[PDB]
Structure formats: C-alpha cells, structure tokens
Amino acid sequence: QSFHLRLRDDKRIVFSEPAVMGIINVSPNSFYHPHLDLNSALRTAEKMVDEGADILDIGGESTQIELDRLLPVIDAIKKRFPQLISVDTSRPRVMREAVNTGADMINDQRALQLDDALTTVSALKTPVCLMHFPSETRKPGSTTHFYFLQSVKKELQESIQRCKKAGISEDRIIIDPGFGQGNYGKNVSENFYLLNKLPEFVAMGLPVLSGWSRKSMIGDVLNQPPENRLFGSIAADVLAVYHGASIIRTHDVKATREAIKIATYTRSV
Amino acid sequence: SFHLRLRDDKRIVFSEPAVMGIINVSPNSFYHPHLDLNSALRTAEKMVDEGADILDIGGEATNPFVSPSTQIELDRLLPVIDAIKKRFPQLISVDTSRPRVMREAVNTGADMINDQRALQLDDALTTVSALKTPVCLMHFPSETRKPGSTTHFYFLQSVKKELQESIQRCKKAGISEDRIIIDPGFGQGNYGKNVSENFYLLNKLPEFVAMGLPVLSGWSRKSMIGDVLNQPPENRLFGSIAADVLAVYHGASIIRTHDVKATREAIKIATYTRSVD
Amino acid sequence: SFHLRLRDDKRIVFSEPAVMGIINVSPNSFYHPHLDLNSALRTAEKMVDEGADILDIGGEPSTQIELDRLLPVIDAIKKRFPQLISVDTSRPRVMREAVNTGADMINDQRALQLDDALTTVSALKTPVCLMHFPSETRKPGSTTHFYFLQSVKKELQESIQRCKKAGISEDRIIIDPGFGQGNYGKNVSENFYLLNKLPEFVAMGLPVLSGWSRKSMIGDVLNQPPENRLFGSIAADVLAVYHGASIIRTHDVKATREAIKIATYTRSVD
Amino acid sequence: SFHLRLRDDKRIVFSEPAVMGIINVSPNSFYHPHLDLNSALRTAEKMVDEGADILDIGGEATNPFVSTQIELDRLLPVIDAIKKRFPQLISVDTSRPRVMREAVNTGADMINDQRALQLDDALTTVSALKTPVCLMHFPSETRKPGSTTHFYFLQSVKKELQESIQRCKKAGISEDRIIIDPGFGQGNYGKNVSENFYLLNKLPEFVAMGLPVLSGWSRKSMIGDVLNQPPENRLFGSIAADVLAVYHGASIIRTHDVKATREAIKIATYTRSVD
Ligand SMILES: Nc1nc(O)c2nc(CNc3ccc(C(=O)O)cc3)cnc2n1
Ligand SMILES: Nc1nc(O)c2nc(CNc3ccc(C(=O)O)cc3)cnc2n1
Ligand SMILES: Nc1nc(O)c2nc(CNc3ccc(C(=O)O)cc3)cnc2n1
Ligand SMILES: Nc1nc(O)c2nc(CNc3ccc(C(=O)O)cc3)cnc2n1
Ligand SMILES: [Cl-]
Ligand SMILES: [Cl-]
Ligand code: NA
Ligand code: NA
Ligand code: NA
C-alpha cells in the first residue's frame, strides 16, 4: 500500500509504505501520556523521531488555552525535525494558527462539522483526516453489525462529498473509521467488526487512517490498564495494515513500524 | 377473534393473531435503520411476500417531551407510507407521538397509530379521537425508573394500572373501544425494565389479555434476548421467535416483528396448541 | 426502612421514615427565622424532645455571614444532642466548614449546581439531598402536568448521574421534588400533581425527601396564614409517606411524626 | 452461645446460633452465581436486611459433580465494597494461602476452608493472620460412597477432624479461632445421601468436640435427591436440615436463605433450650 498527499504548497509527498503517525497529546486530561509542559512534549517528539515516525500528531483539545499548549510545540518541532506535523483539532482558529506555525495537515475527529471548519481547510489547502464520529449520542449495540458498518460508510462518503464540494482536493482527504468507545459511540464487538471489515473503507479510494493504540477495546479484551496494552495494540495495527490501512496513529512508534512492516510483506506477496 | 374499525367504519376481522412487520426509517432507530426510500420499500416488499398483516412505519428523530424535528420525521415517513399505500394491500401503522405527524400520516394512507407514549403528548388524545383510527397504547417508557425498585408483583400491578388508565383516557376522549390496542412495552433502556421484569410480564401476559382488548407484544431482536443468549442483534432470531410463541400462547393478538415469515409460522403452532385447550 | 452511610462509613438504618426538623437562622428565612443563638437552641431542644431524627440548619462577604450564623448553632447542637445534623446550603465553603463543625449531611436546594459543589461533596463523603429546582425562566402552568413531571424526573436523574460520575456513593444520595411556589417555579396544582405522583420519584431507587410544612400551597387551598396551616401540612406529609417518602422536612416535629406513623402502618400492611 | 477472637484480639460473642449467608461470585455455581460486583452487593444488602451475622464470599466455582489471580479479581472488589458498607463479619471461602492473605488484608474477618488448611502454607498463613478459621472435613482421597458402614465412616470423619484441630493448635492457632464442619454434600464431598443424614443425626458427636460447629445443607443434592426437586425448590427440606442441626447444637448455619433460616432456627433454639 503506497499513497501520496499534496501539501499546501502543491508539493506532492509520496509514502512508499504505510505511514506511522506518532501521538503527542498536550492536554493534561488525556487518558495516556499527557504532556504537562513543553519540555516533556519535546522529549517525546525526539524519541518518536528517533523511532522513525513519519508524522507527529499534536493535540490539546477554551480556544486560547488550546493555542497556548499547541503552538509552542508545533513551532519547536517544525524548527528541529523534518517530520510532517498534524494538528488534532476541530476549531477553525486553531487550524489557521497551527498551519501558520507549521502544521502540514489537520486531523479532525469531527470531520469538519464545526461551522467554518470546512471552508477553513479548503482555504488552507492542507490535507485533512476526516474521522467518523456519531452525529450525536448513539446506543452501542443498537443495530446489527452489518447495518452499523453501512451507516459509517454512508456518513464518511457524505463527509468526503462535503469536502469535495467545498473545494478540497481529492489528494488531500484521508478517512478514519474512528476506533474507540465512550463518546465514539461503539462497543467492543463493533470496533472489531469495523477492523475486520476495514477493506470496505479502503475500497472507498482514499488513504485510511486507523488508531487503536492503548485504547479501551484492548483493555477490555485483555483486562489490562493502558500501560499494559502494547502487545494487544500492536496486533490491531498489524491487522489494520494487513487489511490495507495507509496510516497508523500510535503512542508506540518503533513497535508499530516494525510490526506493520511484517503485515505489509504478508499482504504484498 | 378480534377486529379493528378503520376510520371509514370498515371492520377488519382477524381470525388469528396479526403479524405487524417493522420498518424503521430514522438513522438512530433500532436493529435495521432504513437510510433511504428504496431500502424501506425493499423491506416492505419482502415483508408483504412473507405475509405481513400490518406494516409499522416509524421515523422519530427526537423525543417530543424534550418544529424542525417534526418536519424531519414527516420527510422520512410520508414517502414510505405513500409508496406502500399505492403498492400494497397491507394495513399501515404509523409509530409516532406527535399529533401533526399522526394527521399527515393518516391523510397519506396510514390506517392506525402506534404510540409508545400512549397519546400523552399535548393534543394527541383529541387528534386520534378526531382521526377515528385504531390506536395502540403502550406502557409509557420511563427513562428514570430504576428496574428492580419494586417487586415483580408490584411492578406488574403498576403496569396494569397504567394501561387501564390509558384506556380510560381514550374512552373519555371519544375513542371507541374497537380502536384500542394495548401493549405492556417490552424492552430495556428507556423502557425502564430489566431482563427479569420483562420475562415476568411475558409469563403474566394473560393478565393483560383479560382486560378485554387486543394485546400487542414486541420482543423482536431486543436486548432481553441478547442478554440471555449473549448475542448481537443479528443472532437473536430464534430467541425472538420463542418470545413471540409464548406471547401468542398466552393470548397476544398482534406481534410486532422484524422477521415476518418466521414469526408467522412459529405463532401458528402456538395458536394451534392454545386452541386444543 | 432505608439507610444512609455517613462520612466515617458508618451505616445508619432507619426502621421507618425520618423526621427532619427545620431550624432557619437567617433573618429572611421562611416561617420562623431564628434571630439569635439562644432561640435556635430552644427550638432544637423542643424538636429533640418531640422526636426529631435530623435537624436541618439553614442560613442563606455573604458566605462569611452565613457561616457566622450557622456554625455556632451546629457546634452547640453537635455537643448537646445525638440527632443527625443537616446543613441547608449551596455554597461549597459552607458545606466544608459545616461538616468540619459537625454536620452529618448536606441539603442542597440547587442540587450541587454551584461550581465546586460536586467535588466538595464527593470529598466530604457525606450524604447529600438533591432537590429539583426548575429554571427561573419557568412559567408555572405553561406546560401540562404530565409534561412538566417528565422534565422534573429527567432533570433529577441528570443530577443523580452528575453525583455518581463525581464519585458520590449511591447510598449517600437523597432526592426531593422541591415542593413550593414562588422561586420554586410551580403553582398549586403542579405541586399536588407531583405529590400524587410521588411513587414515580420513589421508583428512581433512592430515598425521597418531601417538605410541604407550612408552605403557600396549603395557605392557598385553605385560605390560611402560616400559623393556621398545620392540619393541611400534615395531610401532605401523610400522603407523601404513604406514597413512599423516606424523609419529611417539617417545622412541626411532633405532629408530623405522629401523623406519618399512621401512614407508615397503613402503607406497610400490603 | 459461642465466641470467636478476631485478629485485632477483640472477642465477638453470639448469644444465639449465627446465620452465614452465601455470596458466590464465581460464574459456574449450581445455585446463585454472582457475575458482577453489583449483583453481589444487592445480595449482600438483602442478606444484611434479613439479619445475616456473617457473609461468606467465595470465588471458587462449586459443582461437586465435576487462577489464583482470577479468584482475587472476583473476590477483592466484593470484600472491599462490603467492608465499607456493612458491620457484618466477612468470611472468605478459599483454600489458597495467597487469597487468604489478600482477602484478610482487604477486610475479611475469618477464613472458611473446605480443605481445612491442607494446602501447604495454609496452616502457617492462618496462624500468622490471626483470624478465625472453619475447618471443613473433606475426603483425604477419592472415597467410594457407601463403601463402609455408617458407624465406621463417622469414626473416620471424627478422627480426621480431630487431627485437623490438633494441627491447628500445633501451628499456633488459638482455640477460640477454630470452627469445625462435617462437610455435608455429595459428589467430591465423598458421601452418599444416607451418609450425610447419618452425620446430621449424629451432629452432637461433633458438638461434643468443644468447638463451634458449622453446618451447610442449603439447597444441596441430598435434599434434591430425597424430595426429587431442583435447587430452586429445595427450601423447605433445607430449612428442616438447619432446624435439626441447630437442635443438635450447631453454632453456625451456612445458607442461601437467611430470613427463612433465621426464623426456623429460632424455633429449634427455643425447643432445645426450654429444658
Ligand atoms: N484521526 C484520529 N483517529 C483516532 O482514532 C483518534 N483517536 C483519538 C483518541 N480518542 C479515544 C477514543 C476512545 C478511546 C477509548 O475507548 O479508550 C481512547 C481514545 C484522538 N484523535 C484521533 N484522531
Ligand atoms: N407498540 C410498540 N411496541 C413496542 O414493543 C415497540 N418497540 C419499539 C422499539 N423500542 C425498543 C425498546 C427496547 C429495546 C431493547 O431493549 O433492546 C429495543 C427496542 C418501537 N415501537 C414499539 N411499539
Ligand atoms: N430539601 C429541601 N426541601 C425543601 O422543600 C426545602 N424547602 C425550603 C423552603 N423553601 C420554600 C419554598 C416555597 C415556599 C412556599 O411556596 O410557601 C416556602 C418555602 C428550604 N429548603 C428545602 N430543602
Ligand atoms: N464450611 C463450609 N461448609 C460447607 O457445607 C460448604 N459448602 C460449599 C458448597 N459445596 C457443595 C457440596 C456438595 C453439594 C451437593 O451435594 O449438592 C453442593 C455444594 C462451599 N463451602 C462450604 N463451606
Ligand atoms: Cl424496533
Ligand atoms: Cl423552610
Ligand atoms: Na496497508
Ligand atoms: Na410512538
Ligand atoms: Na374512535
């Protein structure tokens, strides 16, 4: 699985194999490895760069505090490292300033639903990741697995179409089924069903991004706290790439990179 | 047997329990949401071929107790009702709690109204009385009740009392007895019952049947079956059939189901067994 | 029969509905303001002799004023009497200081809506009464009774869920429909409807508290001033207990206690 | 009237036979498995309301007719939640020394061992923990039921229990911390129906050993066999066995049915002591 994106300067970047996107959360309230200051975030960035990350995803999600956290990190990373920078936000103002500070792409868990977001991404000309997120509160397990998958695909296609209409280029759109529980509105079996059926998303023609890293589904199946979820998480990434995923979002860059290389070879014989 | 008197005074006689097939047309609906008109019609066609007596169409977007949503509900319902009215002979039921949806659905061809909230919303009683259609009154779904907070016996008594009051509310409003159907409201979640309470109501269904009106029961694919079998909704067919069988064995008049043919065949055996008394 | 768990983890069981006597220590308080410490203690003494299970003390710069009225009373009561003490307040700081002084539980008419209230009660580990308080923009009578009731239950459920999420133990939550007119945003018939439907609150699975004592809906129905509302008030207490209420908040301890004893017996004989 | 000494050296006195309610948190149990913390707590609340003196929490699946971490994950949360809520004594039904330590550390007041501290380290663990312990008679090996006379079987049971008691005293376990139990049951409890009834009829012989005696017939197969009833229908027969056990001097009754048992044994106690 190879793919490309067109950056905001119309420069084409080609990935010869699935990309690894390392996570740097600067929100003290994150479930895993919150970064409370700039120095600690930069220590993580350096490790991830050493471990071979392709992209670093910086998130800190009330707008000014988000900016005070994100901007210093993006600036420092842009200054020090050659990695592509993704900003994980749903706020148009954050997108604008993040990109002005050096972010190359926008990762939106809300798929540009927040007013002004769509036009903002079109105006910035950056690649964007559209993650599937419930219209509103969904009851997990309330439909068959098949019909749930149908709705996720349908809604992602609608998001893609909104992007194209707003003038976002086809080579700037990444999609993500939005793996997780809690407000991601899925139970464990639904998450695994979407993973099993990932080729149906891949067949939509855009690069697919997948993030299982240390999440509750692994915790539930293994009965392990987040710190003990490494091996289970690696397994999900392997399966995601085996099924055609283009980008893996992870807290564990080296382990993911090595594991998915095996998935790629298995898939590519 | 039982009959329903339609708004034009024609009496539909049912010599055996009726099977009401379900077509949910809201995105947040249970089991199988129909996301467009064509998909809704494919299901109707299947259910018609499987021998449905009634097709129950519902597309509620939001709870009216908590307009744009009214119009959204209409936009989803009317095209399906209209297409079915033109194509098929089946009776059409509209599952809604909104008086305006009731009026427009009936004008479009709906024969009866199915209200989970028992016409409690402002103007619902008067609306149904004026429409002169049969109506199903369900045990009101209490989102705040803590299941198990009373004993099975007392909970059963409270369900019976509430249904008796809903019947009286209807009669006082000028809704005729031959257009009233009652339903103990099987389900968990917002239906304010746990697994054991649901099974207790099912075992005690004859107590609802003795109230003298046709009783409707809907277990199809619901969480009670999932919890007992440890299965997702697509794997609850055989458990659901069993509940329909027992409901009919105990005297239920109408079964509301996602699986028409299977329900129809199974309850025929329940009906025969019940009949040999 | 119900129970609560105090902040020391001690299980308190009530073999029958508890009577909570009211001691208001603010000058603008309802029915009988206690203008000094001595008067408050005389009332406490009477209510203890009359069989009160709990004493609810309430006195709502202004925080400090509330404390100077409350603490001396709570302190005196804590030293002299074995009854449980409740503090009627919405202010986190008053909650902390009152509990530190001897209050066993917190009674919040605002259901811990005031910032820091939730975290404060969770840390204090005391039981808390959550009363429903309709939006102050509400106009009584502008919705049907049934509709209004659903919104009251829904909002109480949301308050309960906030408490649980904040780590407040289920055996430390009491709920209250918030009987009253005026700023309680209800009219006479809405109050009687909630009373008639009280078993629907009991069905939420937590002890229910009710307070009709001397209130305006009795005054309006009987055309009586506060002094003449005793017989109507106990009638409301009787009905509340008959419908399953666990705690009755009253200015008239002896009369309420005796009346609800009859209600409890009648309810109990299934 | 009997007494026990808790590990805090405080003596607890029972003026009448104590009722021990059963809370099993294992998925595979023949009667009322508790599969989650909440169900276990509901049962506990009900049993406390009904007047239970002791709650016996077990995480080992009990089917007589057919990992340490898994037992702890089921038990500890329940024991913790009970310790924080109720004044009742907490018993932990386990044979695993590690479980004994962790359960006691979490709040268990005594240890109920169906193996009478046979597993290595169990003896020394209980002596060091300083908690009361119930020693239940269990087949040293696979016994064939009905293979000896009733009298000779009883002799072996009494001899083996006496050996167990002696092992405990030698290990330094206090005499006011030892409870004994004839181990009523079939299957791997190594007895048939007649043998169980013989032991019950002869309960006074265990009572004469000078330690409080615990007895557990609740909804067991002996009742099922005699009445031809599934577990749900064994209440009345179970009550009868409890009545006889108490009439013969049992100090503790282990039951799934607290209120019914308490009421029945009050009658037994009245009759026994009217003298
Ligand atoms: N594109 C994209 N894709 C994701 O998967 C993602 N996940 C998070 C993290 N959000 C969650 C959700 C659920 C859970 C749990 O159940 O454990 C954990 C973390 C943040 N940004 C994200 N962005
Ligand atoms: N007359 C009537 N009778 C019903 O039984 C019914 N059920 C639904 C569907 N509602 C539910 C409720 C609970 C559950 C669960 O626990 O799984 C599922 C679906 C919609 N209209 C209904 N109408
Ligand atoms: N938990 C609880 N429950 C109450 O019922 C209550 N009432 C008051 C007193 N408030 C009112 C409200 C209305 C009226 C009237 O209309 O007469 C009188 C007094 C103060 N704290 C209270 N706390
Ligand atoms: N002290 C003590 N005393 C018991 O009697 C006991 N029983 C069990 C449960 N074990 C059984 C054995 C046999 C049977 C049957 O034949 O039905 C049923 C249950 C677990 N802990 C126990 N602990
Ligand atoms: Cl449905
Ligand atoms: Cl007052
Ligand atoms: Na791939
Ligand atoms: Na409805
Ligand atoms: Na009519």
Image (cartoon, coloured by chain):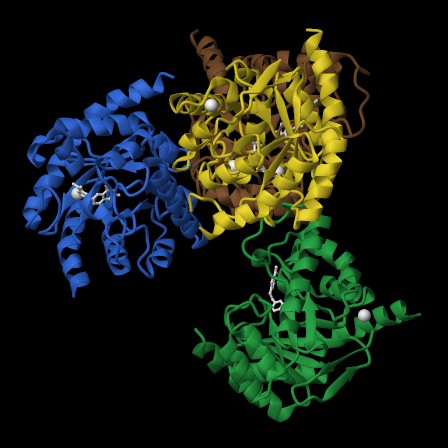
Chain colours: A green, B yellow, C blue, D brown
* Residue D6 appears in the picture as rendered: yes
**B264 versus B88 height, above or below:** above
Q: Nearer the viewer, residue D250 or D177?
A: D250
Is residue A62 toward the left or the right of residue C212 in the image? right
The quadrant of the image that shows the N terminus of chain B is top right
The quadrant of the image that shows the C terminus of chain B is top right
Residue D274 occupies quadrant: top left
Q: Nearer the viewer, residue B158 or A143?
A: A143
Name which residue lies at 24% across and 50% down: C102
Residue D112: give x, y in percent of width and height. 60, 34
Is residue B71 toward the left or the right of residue D201 in the image? left
Q: Nearer the viewer, residue B155 or B117?
A: B117
Residue A155: give x, y in percent of width and height. 65, 60
Residue reaching furthest bottom? A79
Is residue A63 toward the left or the right of residue C260 in the image? right
Name which residue lies at 46% across and 41% down: B100
Residue D246: give x, y in percent of width and height. 53, 16
Q: Nearer the viewer, residue C1 or C139?
A: C139
Residue B84: give x, y in percent of width and height. 66, 38
* Residue D35 appears in the picture as rendered: no
How many tags in the picture? 0
